[PDB]
Length: 222
Image 1 (cartoon, rainbow, N blue to C red):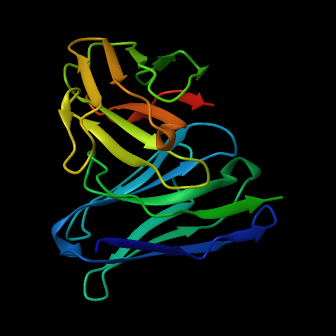
Image 2: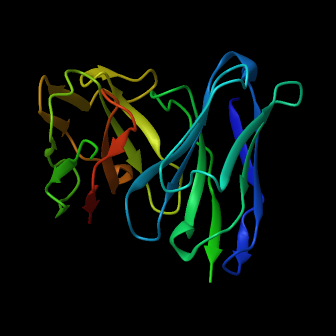
């Protein structure tokens, strides 16, 4: 029932402007903070910005400060990202995400084409397995992040999906073949019996310190 319908993206020249809208439904939109996260073509995830529930406090990444602006309408339940002075580096698929750092829901994304922190290293980068295989991915943190670690799943051309939160807690509605473990700087995501719908790129994310940093990714191919 929860829906995050994104629109506004497209093709633009350097210096142009765009307005992304993320219309939300199926929940009390004004009861939660929202975020914009972008993914460059073929690369990992990058937190763009975030706005609180009432729309008062706004946070931005250093690369988009002064040019991008987050806003929200709580009567129409819609998120907004104004993008001026666009650069080719801003070329990415932009998703809107719910809740401060949990990111329990993501929108299908909108494509925008313009033409110091905690590092997260994932091991292995890629792997090829078959149905029923046991897969074990490792996320290593440059600093101790305690249990502030989330595992997301991203099937090709689709939106990311929250799988594990708090390093080991399983998100409601996710199959039990997914396990998270880890305490300090090393975490492991375990798929006990790989099924055909698991072939996808799995990411780890820290939120111990801001801004949230994602892992390089782990592509589980066939």
